Length: 220
Ligand code: NA
Image (cartoon, rainbow, N blue to C red; front, side, top):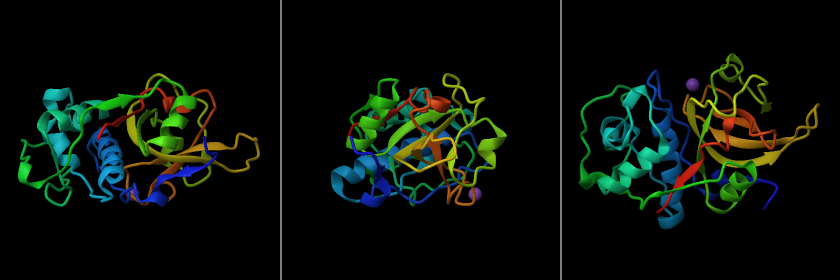
């Protein structure tokens, strides 16, 4: 595999969004991964509707602003036969009744692929597929105040993840500790968080914060 990958450079990645005060991170991770696999297929990058997932993918196991899973969103899109665009079904950060309209669908998928629980396999997936949906333990003050550099939190758990985000690549930079590898992660807390809304999460450090534990992508 390459030592460095950044799918934003290949046009796979929409700008950073902001979920507000709704527990819908899973919808943003999912749209992020489907935006990538749709681009891969069609060569067109279209922002997808998290509200569509929030309002409508309850039958697949999701619970709106109370939480969800990217794989359940991927299943909804297959079951539903479509997903509306962000422009047509904009984000309101509250759960409402489903207003999906197939005429405004701009995306589809035929299931999803779960990546084996290993950073080595996650790396191979990111290198060959595109942006990957992943779950992390973001429940630490250090994560809130992140500004730059490689994020490493010694109290981070590799099993109890609470936040869906999107790995758009990986790389390295020299550090004091010589723990130099990172996953490049798109968040959904707006541009003012982190590095323009991105975080470099420690890579090949014993599955730091569980980044490889629940990784998947939609099959388009
Ligand atoms: Na922000």
